[PDB]
Image (cartoon, rainbow, N blue to C red; front, side, top):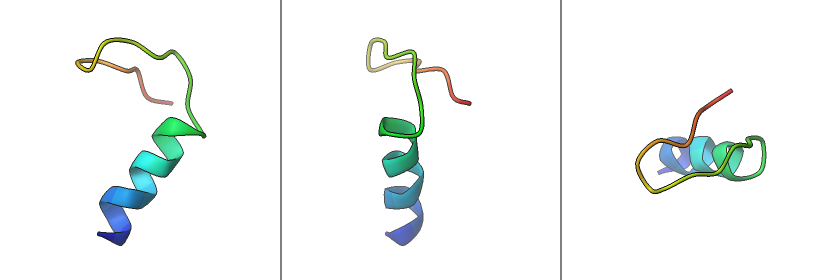
Length: 27
């Protein structure tokens, strides 16, 4: 819950390079 949400919240705001729902490079 707090984990999956945290990661996503960071991969949506604290991340870039948006692509198809099958990749989205992480940083």
